[PDB]
Amino acid sequence: RTQTGNNTTVNIIISTVDYLLRVQESISDFYWYYSGKDVIDEQGQRNFSKAIQVAKQVFNTLTEYIQGPCTGNQQSLAHSRLWDAVVGFLHVFAHMQMKLSQDSSQIELLKELMDLQKDMVVMLLSMLEGNVVNGTIGKQMVDMLVESSNNVEMILKFFDMFLKLKDLTSSDTFKEYDPDGKGVISKRDFHKAMESHKHYTQSETEFLLSCAETDENETLDYEEFVKRFHEPAKDIGFNVA
């Protein structure tokens, strides 16, 4: 952050967040390109992977900067332009978290994006390490969240809609629909399960059915479905909470 002895000082902490802000804008533009189109091609999916890797590394560098309650680094990044990058990533996450889930060919991209979200939330947690009551960092973070209100609402609804999935699949009402231990429920019986659960609204039920991949047998493995959509929700949502 500061080279005391040297005549001239260069703020690497601010240069890193400037690069993060540039790369987040690039990712947002590339998403806006790939928004209207139904399916993402292989080249686009690979470019997303490389950009997500770069952003993940930058986030890890920043969180390594701001651990060991480095007060100077924390204050500098609080006054820097990090909040714009965070509010951009929040929008990108909130929309791709709708979009990639419906398609069954973007599982790897979805995992990369949910890992990037976890790292961003970890850096946000490290931002508040050793916080004081009514702190400037807390106030700026609340302002950033308020600016990104809608995206946080959609992310939190997505997380809840899949956190209730474990309770649904471990409930006895599901066991009487599937009395066998094979774990491959039919798509028809799965919809009857969502209807009987009556903890899921019609929109949530139809979205979960759409996001459920089924083979030519018209049956899906609910075990694999929950084992794909539950743990990322759990680990990211715990840090958000």
Image (cartoon, helix red, strand yellow):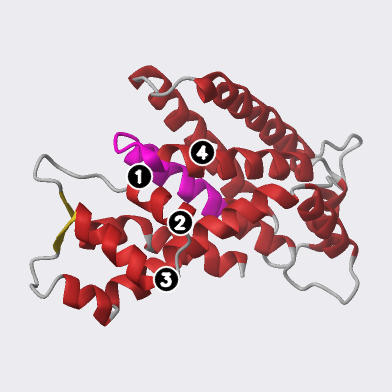
Coordinates of residue 237 in the picture (x, y in percent): 54, 65
Disc 4 or 1, which lies upstream in sequence?
A: 4
Circle 3 residues within 10 Å: few <14, some 14–19, many ≥20: few
The kind of residue on which mark 4 rests is Met
The kind of residue on which mark 1 rests is Ser
- Residue that numbered label 1 is attached to: 210
Which range of residues does the magenta coloring cover? 101-119
What is the C-alpha distance between the residues marked 1 and 2? Answer: 12 Å
Circle 1 residues within 10 Å: few <14, some 14–19, many ≥20: few
The kind of residue on which mark 3 rests is Lys
Of the 4 image quadrants, the one containing the C terminus is bottom right
| Front of the two marks 4 and 2 | 2
- The residue positioned 40% from the left and 26% from the top of the image is 45
Q: Find numbered disc 1 in the image and state the secondary structure of the residue it sits on.
A: helix
Q: Please indicate whether residue 225 sits to the left or right of residue 203 in the image.
A: left
The reply to whether callout 3 and callout 1 are in contact (CB within 8 Å) is no
Disc 4 or 2, which lies upstream in sequence?
A: 4
- Residue that numbered label 3 is attached to: 198
- Residue that numbered label 2 is attached to: 202
What is the C-alpha distance between the residues marked 2 and 3? Answer: 9 Å
Let me know if residue 110 is in the magenta part.
Answer: yes
